[PDB]
Amino acid sequence: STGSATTTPIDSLDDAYITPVQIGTPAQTLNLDFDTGSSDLWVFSSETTASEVDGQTIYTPSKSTTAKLLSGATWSISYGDGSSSSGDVYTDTVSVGGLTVTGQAVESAKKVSSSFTEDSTIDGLLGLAFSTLNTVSPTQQKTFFDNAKASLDSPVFTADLGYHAPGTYNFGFIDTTAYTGSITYTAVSTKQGFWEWTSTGYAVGSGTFKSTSIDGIADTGTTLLYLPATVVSAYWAQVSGAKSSSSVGGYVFPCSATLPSFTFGVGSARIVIPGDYIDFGPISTGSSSCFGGIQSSAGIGINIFGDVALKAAFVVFNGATTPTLGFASK
Picture (tube, helix red, strand yellow):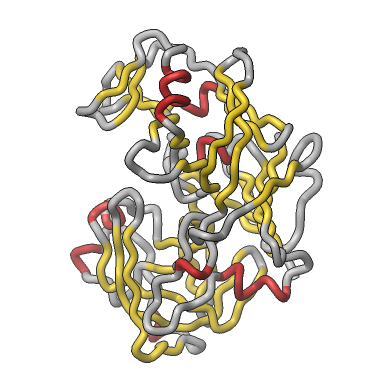
């Protein structure tokens, strides 16, 4: 089997991407944030504290003839951005782009933090990291991909995120029309539960490539590119007037600037992030200070190849017995 679903930016900045997901019988379609940095499929629901729902579409398990309470199971998750959610668990039928999993754990939120409430466009998350990170207790649950894998034509999924445009998540096949050149594959460590890999270096604009190992994670659920402070300083030094602002929470730059590209290495291959992908717009409405899309990972404890990086590539998440990651230009 295979599946193919379009993923759509939630706003004009590509802050996140939503993908429609069918849950239950009859189907209830929710727009979920596919997150290769976490491993829980959780949704706003009829159980979510009413004051914490503000415009989201909810899953109502009592209206699904295939929903079953997973007795005694609870979940609770905290994300890198400080947001969180928790609740109980159902199993139900879940379909993405025509690919169906029966008995998928659907984690129903009883509580969500303010950032989730405040974002009316995201109805929940669909985790695509390794199932070892799943938070369900006392019996850990599998991700949608883990459950689907054996049925797939090939044990893979691909992320093809758009810049200010829709893109695609495919399951079970590689669309050879969706990229240019070849796909370069690179090793993955699953030791921390992430799609963790080592980039071979970087360049700023038309500058020379610096060969240096940068360990980080491929994370579709993180907006920006978080890299070591040395790398980030080298990038922003090429933008007149750019500075790190403690008050704003990162590097800012004059909105009048033209940003240089940023290249990262994948083995001997190179992925080029155009400068415009690094512009996250005014820090507040009407400001002429703009927020940068490349930020320091110092004090996160891990480097993160978030959407800024991933949307410059066609990315293969290869879930074979020994997982690997592939990157192609597009």
